[PDB]
Image: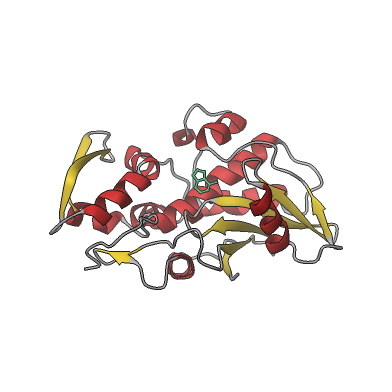
């Protein structure tokens, strides 16, 4: 399994664009695509995972472990007192947990557990972060940089600190890779913090339905329209692939053939 590094401390728009491109190209199936949009692999393709190393301005890092089939963050590691400290979500199966241990921290004599004692659903992360909606957790490059430093090499931190980091990182890494729209929100706001708008949230929550709708579309027409939100919180009834393709970075894996095109 490969590691993609993003230097948050020295980030520029172009370096984030390159990061997104690299992450999409490592995660995607080598071949699968629908309507020109690359698709993630089935859950049997190896390697099953990708690592994403995030570097702060002090050169400390956190490495996220992502599942290729759905781009979920499974856990993260940091160097702590010389040790590979691995932090696994509590919703990972026994067999995948072994893989997380061994992928984040391959040397079994130099590693140390520090569990994430909660699941990785946004509802849970929001709860831990003290917010009723992740619209209330700002995203941004300086925020990500700061949050890495609250955790990496730090003996103890609160669940709120951890959940904030995870909400920021999940959205700026996995959601941005899945959605060019979200990558572009980061780029448009590159020099500042921002709050995810209703379209960011609607895309995040509907990626599986969107991916299925694109995979199933015939001659560019969705079989069933899909109702999303625009950035101004008005309904967006998507009728055609060409309406939503610009916002897409990766499709969730969907079995069967599609117009590739
Ligand atoms: N752990 C995770 N990783 C990626 N996307 C997510 N969406 C919700 N939780 C997530």
Q: Is residue 109 left or right of residue 46?
A: right
The answer to whether one can see residue 238 in this image is no
| Front-most of residues 192 and 201 | 201
Residue displayed at 63% across by 48% down: 147
Q: Position of residue 227 (x, y in %)?
A: 23, 37
Q: Position of residue 238 (x, y in %)?
A: 19, 44
Question: Relative to 118, does residue 250 appear above or below in the rendering?
Answer: below
Residue displayed at 66% across by 39% down: 161
Question: Relative to 81, does residue 198 appear above or below in the rendering?
Answer: above
| Front-most of residues 19 and 255 | 255
Instruction: Please give the count of numbered marks on the rendered protein.
Output: 0
| Front-most of residues 92 and 9 | 92
Q: In which quadrant of the rendered view does residue 234 lie?
A: top left
Q: Is residue 63 left or right of residue 245?
A: right
Q: Position of residue 25 (x, y in %)?
A: 44, 70
Q: Quadrant of the C terminus?
A: bottom left
The answer to whether one can see residue 125 in this image is yes
Residue displayed at 25% across by 62% down: 258
Question: Relative to 216, does residue 228 appear above or below in the rendering?
Answer: above
| Front-most of residues 240 and 169 | 240
């Amino acid at each position: 399994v490969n590691t993609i590094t993003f230097d948050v401390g020295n980030a520029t728009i172009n370096k984030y664009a390159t990061f997104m491109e690299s992450l999409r190209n490592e995660a995607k199936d080598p071949t699968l695509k629908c309507y020109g949009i690359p698709m993630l692999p089935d859950s049997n393709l190896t390697p099953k995972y990708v690592l994403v190393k995030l570097q702060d301005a002090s050169s400390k890092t956190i490495t996220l472990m992502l599942r290729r089939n759905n781009l979920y963050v499974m856990g993260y590691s940091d160097l702590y007192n010389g040790k590979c400290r691995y932090h696994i979500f509590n919703d990972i199966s026994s067999t995948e947990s072994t893989d997380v241990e061994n992928t984040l921290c391959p040397n079994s004599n130099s590693r140390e557990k520090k569990a994430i004692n909660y699941n990785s659903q946004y509802s849970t992360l929001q709860n831990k972060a003290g917010v009723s909606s992740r619209s209330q957790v700002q995203l941004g490059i300086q925020i990500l940089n700061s949050d890495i430093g609250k955790i990496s090499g730090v003996s103890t931190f609160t669940d709120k600190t951890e959940a904030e980091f995870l909400l920021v990182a999940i959205q700026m890494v996995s959601e941005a890779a899945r959605f060019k729209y979200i990558e572009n929100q980061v780029k448009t706001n590159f020099n500042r913090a921002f709050n995810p708008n209703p379209k960011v949230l609607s895309l995040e929550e509907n990626w599986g339905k969107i991916s299925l709708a694109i995979h199933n579309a015939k001659n560019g027409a969705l079989t069933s329209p899909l109702e999303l939100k625009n950035a101004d919180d008005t309904k967006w009834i998507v009728l055609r692939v060409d309406e939503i393709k610009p916002d897409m970075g990766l499709l969730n894996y969907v079995s069967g053939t599609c117009q590739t095109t």
